Image (cartoon, rainbow over all chains, first blue to last red; front, top):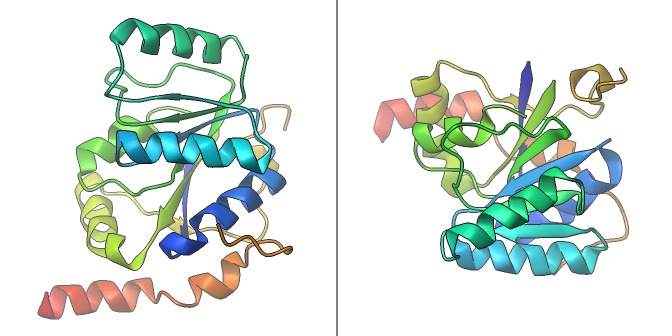
Length: 161
Length: 30
């Protein structure tokens, strides 16, 4: 029940792409992954400049800070969460129906821990430099990540549908 | 930082990546 897609972008395109996703997807809540703590804080600052509420969570924080933020997220205080690879036992927030890999992971085990489990969309931002990791992860998981279509069926991720 | 006034062109940009052809090149040479 998670539909996986990729957009092909360059680093300089990623934010405009992300703004278009925010604009056109029927997001209830979303989780956005980056490949480091520093880039997480950078993207949270940027999402806030584009107009969207977000929280953020990363490896360089006290555990209890992270727990409270995530409890505040679960209760709907913000609509988007920006984070690093914090999930071990899966994502059990029901309202999250769109997960975004702002940075594509390197390892298949990283990718699995991001994408289990939003009905939901997993949208991958793929650069030329991610090409080997895309192939490796597709092969290891036994999965296909399809190109993002111009119209995403609402029945794939909006629960009223 | 670069944000045009129009929606991001997903479709044009996906034409810049011939996924199945790249993968085959990867398997052949890389």
